[PDB]
Amino acid sequence: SNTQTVLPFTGLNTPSGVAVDSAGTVYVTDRGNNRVVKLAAGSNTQTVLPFTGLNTPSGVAVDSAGTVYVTDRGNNRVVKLAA
Amino acid sequence: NTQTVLPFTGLNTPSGVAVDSAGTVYVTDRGNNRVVKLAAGSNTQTVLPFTGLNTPSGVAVDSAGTVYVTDRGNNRVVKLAA
Amino acid sequence: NTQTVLPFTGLNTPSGVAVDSAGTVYVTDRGNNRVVKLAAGSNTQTVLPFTGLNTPSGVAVDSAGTVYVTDRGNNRVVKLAA
Image 1 (cartoon, helix red, strand yellow):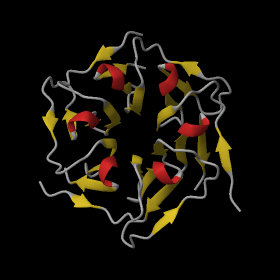
Image 2 (cartoon, each protein chain N blue to C red; image 1 turned 60 degrees about the vertical axis):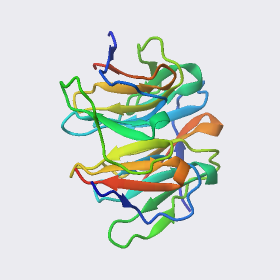
Image 3 (cartoon, helix red, strand yellow; image 1 turned 90 degrees about the horizontal axis):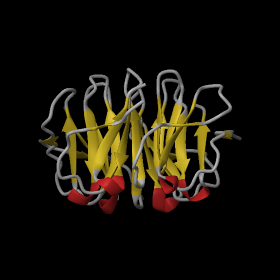
């Protein structure tokens, strides 16, 4: 027998991509809501990252400085946001 | 400039990939509602014991070998400890 | 904070993204059947020499710089060494 854990993100619609940084913060592209949300390790409350003008964001990555990169699928671009 | 096709089998619309420190490769096998992994060396493919996935879309693995999946069809994010 | 747009060119439905320890950004340019990368500080992307992709959906990179891609339309996973 095994255990899987549902992360306490809220109000997701068609989540499309996930990244995890060195601190254990989890970042998710909430595709159907045109937004990117995150949850700190231990934290109970998701925060919405201040990207703008997203259309169907499809993927997310985070580098060693905590910069977050997102593929903005509907706008044919990749956007990044410093920590 | 030679690419190598990995010995995964039975994939249907694979949607995401992650690789851990040991070189194990994890794939969200979206059309089969599962996540599979391929062990380095042995090339043994196993299905990760997630349950109730619907069109999983993205996967990540952290330094502790915890696997995170976006369970797209169920509007949730799930993880599985090593 | 204010977002920055990376100087990729000609993307069509980019589907996935990874960044390695060197800050190189790798993107699956799904609608163009290709994978592109941008070195930190560069303004000119390079197209990785994969072959025969059909709607690549996700990308990962390991510590040796090997790039892994889910080639969604061909139900396979391919890799290319650095």
